[PDB]
Image (tube, coloured by chain):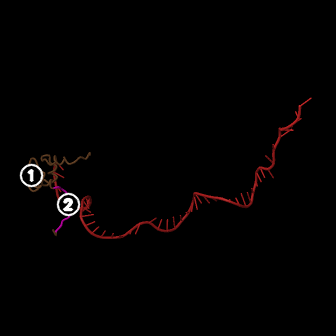
Amino acid sequence: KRRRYTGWGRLSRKLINGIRDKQSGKTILDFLKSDGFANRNFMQLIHDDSLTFKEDIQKAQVSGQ
DNA sequence: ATGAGACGCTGGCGATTAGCTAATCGCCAGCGTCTCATCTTTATGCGCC
């Protein structure tokens, strides 16, 4: 309790270990921790039609509100 | 069977009498702090469809 922290990150918890992938069944943290032959980076994970992430982030909000 | 109709110094002074914006420039402008947290964003540094 004597120790106190300040600051906040940039990403949610549901994004790291909440949202799972349809084809895999593992989260983003797992893909970064292990992806086998091609240890693809964050931008390759998100911008991949082979995974579901690009599809599920697009449900975001509405810019034309 | 008679008794109306026909009307001035003013203009050019002084001298009261009364009254008003405008052009020029200068001055001089509330300000002092701290705490606390909060978020951003930037400089540099690392990845190929």
Q: Residue B8: image x %, image y %?
A: 81, 48
Is A4 magenta? The answer is yes
Quadrant of the drawing holding the N terminus of chain A: bottom left
Chain of residue at mark 2? A
Q: Colour of chain A?
A: brown
Bounds of the magenta span? A3-12
Q: Is residue A7 left or right of residue A25?
A: right
Q: Residue B14: image x %, image y %?
A: 74, 60
First-in-chain label (2 vs 1): 2
Q: Residue A49: image x %, image y %?
A: 14, 46
Q: Is residue B29 left or right of residue A58?
A: right
Determine the main secondary structure of the stretch shown in magenta. Answer: loop
Amino acid marked by disc 1: Lys
Q: Colour of chain B?
A: red
Q: Which residue lies furthest to the left in this view?
A: A36
Amino acid marked by disc 2: Trp
Up the image or down, A55 lies above or below B38; here it is above
Is the C-beta separation of discs 2 and 1 under 8 Å?
no
Crowd class of label 1 (few under 14; some 14 to 19; many from 20; radius 10 Å): some
Q: In this view, does B31 lie to the left or right of B34?
A: right
Up the image or down, B21 lies above or below A4; here it is above
Crowd class of label 2 (few under 14; some 14 to 19; many from 20; radius 10 Å): few
Residue holding disc 2? A8
x 9%, y 55%: residue: A30
Label 2: which secondary element:
loop
Q: Is residue B34 left or right of residue B45?
A: right
Chain of residue at mark 1? A
Instruction: Choose between A41 and B21: the one closer to the eye.
Output: B21
Residue holding disc 1? A26
x 13%, y 47%: residue: A52
